[PDB]
Amino acid sequence: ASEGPALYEDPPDQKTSPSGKPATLKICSWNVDGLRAWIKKKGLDWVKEEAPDILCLQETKCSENKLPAELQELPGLSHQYWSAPSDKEGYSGVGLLSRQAPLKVSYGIGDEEHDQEGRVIVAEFDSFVLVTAYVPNAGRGLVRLEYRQRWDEAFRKFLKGLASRKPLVLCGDLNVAHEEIDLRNPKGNKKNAGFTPQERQGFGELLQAVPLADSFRHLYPNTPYAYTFWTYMMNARSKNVGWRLDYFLLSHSLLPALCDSKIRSKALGSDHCPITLYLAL
């Protein structure tokens, strides 16, 4: 192809806020490409080293009634909530695992049409509400793009509702690289899932409407070659031909508490890498 390797070294963890407050909350999000596969690939060992307060997982591909026993070897994340497709099949799926129990856990976005594929978990805490999401892919041939646009609108309105009540943290695989800086090959992907004008625009609408700020891009507005997904094919990860599909979006009110937003480039076990947020809440 046209791309050789493009170097990217995620900056050291900045663990104090702009006002000097140490981070009190570390949240990790990871599209795991199958809970079972990932666990086999030692994903949990990496989680233990990272020691997040909250872990959010996407594409667990796992029935809520078929959770791997290994998930009980996680004492520091003993509160575990799962949402999988209603049809009880093994695809899509999200998880949220927390050191402390949330005040309330909910599933979906309150729209039956969009709530059957196990894509959203809402965990309300004292000072903020956390949402993790696995956003519907636009599909091969963009065959699912029309549905995706419906999803984007419903999701945006739902989140605007949440934020009207409490400061909001949204994380997960949002299945779009927002701008050209967010993927290695913008030119060749504008008609492919993840970089259509429609998807990018939906992301833009999401930021202004809630509103929300892109934590990573806020901190690193001019930083290129920072990605969270690489196709398993074509030796893409080795050449850093990737996409930033995984985000932490924050209510503006939370920006003063933002310490850092990390991309765990070296962490193996999926075709996405983990991302990690430090907040001083």
Image (tube, rainbow, N blue to C red):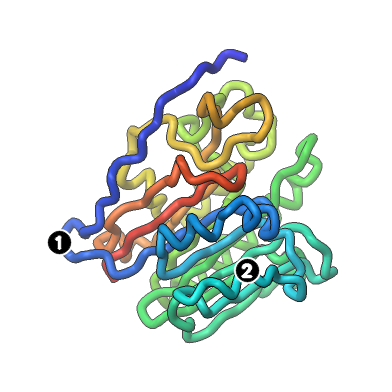
Q: Secondary structure at mark 2?
A: helix
Tell me if I can see residue 210 in this picture: no
Residue 49 lies in quadrant: bottom left
Q: Residue at x 79, y 35 (%)?
A: 141
For label 2, the residue is: 70
Q: Secondary structure at mark 1?
A: loop
Name the residue type under label 1: Gly
Determine whether 227 is above or below 89 in the image: above
Mark 2 surroundings: few (<14), some (14-19) or many (≥20) residues within 10 A: few
Tell me if I can see residue 198 in this picture: yes
Residue 229: give x, y in percent of width and height.
56, 40
Residue nearest the observer in this picture, 179 or 130: 130
Q: Residue at x 52, y 78 (%)?
A: 78
Name the residue type under label 2: Glu
For label 1, the residue is: 20
Location of the N terminus by quadrant is top right
| Label 1 or label 2, whichever comes before in sequence order | 1
In the shown orientation, is residue 62 left or right of residue 100? right
Residue 74: give x, y in percent of width and height.
52, 72
Q: Residue at x 61, y 53 (%)?
A: 32
* Callout 1 touching callout 2 (CB < 8 Å): no
Residue 40: give x, y in percent of width and height.
65, 55
User: Cα distance, mark 1 to mark 2?
Assistant: 38 Å
Determine whether 222 is above or below 105 in the image: above
View extreme (left): residue? 20
In the shown orientation, is residue 105 left or right of residue 114? left
Residue nearest the observer in this picture, 120 or 81: 81
Residue nearest the observer in this picture, 240 or 189: 240
